[PDB]
Image (cartoon, rainbow, N blue to C red):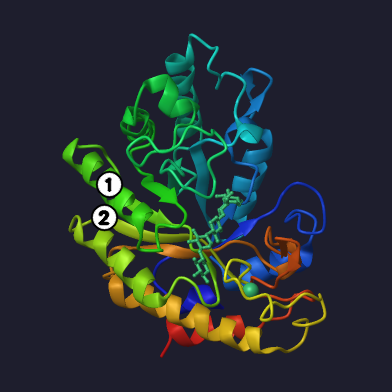
Amino acid sequence: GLASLADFPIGVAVAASGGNADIFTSSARQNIVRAEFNQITAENIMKMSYMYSGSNFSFTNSDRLVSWAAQNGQTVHGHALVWHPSYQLPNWASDSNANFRQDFARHIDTVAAHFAGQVKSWDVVNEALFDSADDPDGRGSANGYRQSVFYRQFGGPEYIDEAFRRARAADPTAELYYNDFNTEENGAKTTALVNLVQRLLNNGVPIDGVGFQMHVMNDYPSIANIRQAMQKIVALSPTLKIKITCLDVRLNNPYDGNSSNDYTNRNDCAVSCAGLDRQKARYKEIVQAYLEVVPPGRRGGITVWGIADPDSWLYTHQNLPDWPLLFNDNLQPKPAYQGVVEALSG
Ligand SMILES: O[C@@H]1[C@@H](O)[C@H](O[C@@H]2CO[C@@H](O[C@@H]3CO[C@@H](O[C@@H]4CO[C@@H](O[C@@H]5CO[C@@H](O)[C@H](O)[C@H]5O)[C@H](O)[C@H]4O)[C@H](O)[C@H]3O)[C@H](O)[C@H]2O)OC[C@H]1O
Ligand SMILES: [Ca+2]
């Protein structure tokens, strides 16, 4: 499979919350994972609040998943130690909690140590950079940073240095990553990413790599921009690893101001359509760019955000249908799969 063509991790995100995509329930899914990948990231059950039952830590479900990975030839990328969305915020993560810094420290110390020798790498901090298109806190940019509880409670971006230092100490073997989305656009956010990373280096913070989520569209951003944005980070240090963490490719772009080029029916690209062919080229050009811009030895891996199209968080987005992954509705490989195979080979 895919994993056999590369010398760095080729992973996929797995559902584990009941439903058709549940990894423990779908043997067809388990067979794809076993045949094509060598690493898995929990799509949801490893987020912050899932580590607790009320105010006590509860690792039962995540342990079941980590254990399944190990028995099925997969390493595990942890997503994520720190992240802002209220739906997954532990109950202590509040502006009213006077013990915030202590509870924050306990969180990192405990879960990083708990999984110490079973998790290969971690999204230590995820989505700390401000983003004009996703500011639920409503506070605006604080010098490029998103003003989440963590930023507020610590009075600045130092919560980031702390998370990394904390994680490194609890698990000296895990690769520590900063992860985020839109930083491949090569725009404002890319610039902020560069400053954030530079700051961390200057401070001697133990960061091992930078993850690019890569939630792109068939035609945006251009690979020329994706290339550069990756280049800029690669250039900041001689050892920093680059990891594509949540790759997926939408055939529909609802921000282009052209509604005439949108597939609005589930049947449009169920079998064959121009977008599916462009998606083969799109996946290909991206992996190629990764291979050419990131030096061997600095390759953290490429992870696709899901197994089959219907499992995708983008199966439907902006009220439009989409077919974002490598495997279709029937668990058959799509042209996107071939694009990956060709890029990884020759
Ligand atoms: O744990 C996981 C979470 O990490 C994950 O988080 C979501 C990640 O994606 C976020 O949404 C993104 C919002 O920004 C969009 O980009 C816009 C798109 O439009 C661009 O501008 C136009 C593009 O088209 C051209 O034609 C036109 O010329 C351009 O002007 C604009 O510049 C971009 O910034 C991304 O497409 C979205 O992915 C989302 O908010 C996060 O929640 O969610 C899953 C979870 O598992
Ligand atoms: Ca459109």
In this orientation, which residue lies closer to the viewer: 27 or 319? 319
On whether ligand 1 comes within 8 Å of the CB at mark 2, the answer is no
Q: In the figure, is residue 292 to the left or right of 59?
A: left
Q: Is residue 183 positioned above or below 331 on the image?
A: above
Which quarter of the rendering shows the C terminus?
bottom left
* Identity of the residue drawn at 73% across and 65% down: 29
Tell me where residue 39 appears, x and y as whole percent: 53, 60
Q: Label 1 is placed on what type of residue? A: Val
Q: Label 2 is placed on what type of residue? A: Leu
Q: Are marks 1 and 2 in contact (CB under 8 Å)?
A: yes
In this orientation, which residue lies closer to the viewer: 99 or 66? 99
Mark 2 is surrounded, within 10 Å at the Cα level, by few (under 14), some (14 to 19) or many (20 or more) other residues, namely some
Label 2 element class:
loop
Instruction: Determine which quarter of the picture holds residue 294.
Output: bottom left
Residue bearing the label numbered 1: 197
Residue 70 seen = no
Disc assigned to residue 259 = none
* Identity of the residue drawn at 72% across and 49% down: 16
Residue 54 seen = yes
Instruction: Determine which quarter of the picture holds residue 108.
Output: top left
Q: Is residue 274 positioned above or below 336 on the image?
A: below
Tell me where residue 256 appears, x and y as whole percent: 57, 71
Tell me where residue 225 appears, x and y as whole percent: 36, 71
Label 1 vs label 2, nearer the camera: 1
Q: In the figure, is residue 252 to the left or right of 2?
A: right
Tell me where residue 309 appears, x and y as whole percent: 71, 69
Q: Is residue 88 positioned above or below 244 on the image?
A: above
- The quarter of the rendering in which ligand 1 is drawn is bottom right
* Identity of the residue drawn at 81% across and 76% down: 265
Residue bearing the label numbered 2: 240
